[PDB]
Image (cartoon, rainbow, N blue to C red; front, side):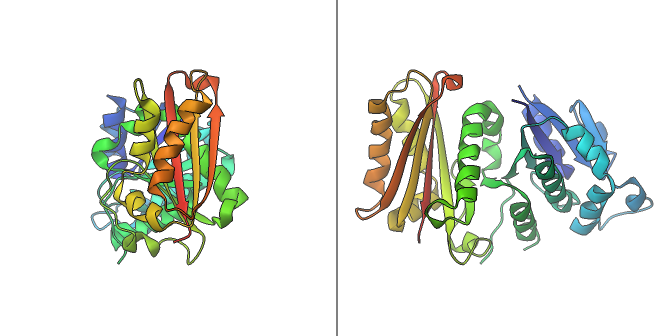
Length: 295
């Protein structure tokens, strides 16, 4: 399976470069100056015509249209990808507008598309606007802190299994879920300021944990419900979807070690679906996803 990490804009090119220091990287920008600082092997300047003689003040809309203009070139850089990771990293600029369009393009190619947001936002507004557009355009949105960025590439295969699970849940509409946001690590986010992006009903929150070695099942399950969002939400949650995936060394009894951690954290009357996959391509790592819904 081919994975592609796409960095869009000032922040995204800076995101890609830190990650570069088994994944193809692609750097997209309306600003060709920034494109020369990229160590990406494949770089794409978008909106050459639209941006001629432009100066400061470049907004999201410029970048959105710019990406539509260079659509074919974006398609040729994504050709053959099974999964795609798109980020516009920190900061503003044109990437905020372009990154959704890039995501939308890869989806119509049929790649599983994941939006990575590291830029702080709150909804209780320019950054926040960008987050909403990304979320309409991707299969799954994951919010993660910037200092934890390297995890999405360091544990890309476990996190691959997590986003497939999220894409499956969101399309089947399991337990009525119609809208889903994923979280990794300690995020500065509050339910209040996320409930606005998400649906009036059927919204869900997914935590992820990946771990290996001694006590791995329990530490993954712990990591999964550790971020503020999950910690608060899983308590009142009416439904919980739990999944642990591992390779041949995982046994049902180890899996159950994780399921117990989560079940102790959800309240007593929860409707909890617990799944366990043994998947050889995982080797020695395990991934725990905990999906909460029904707030």
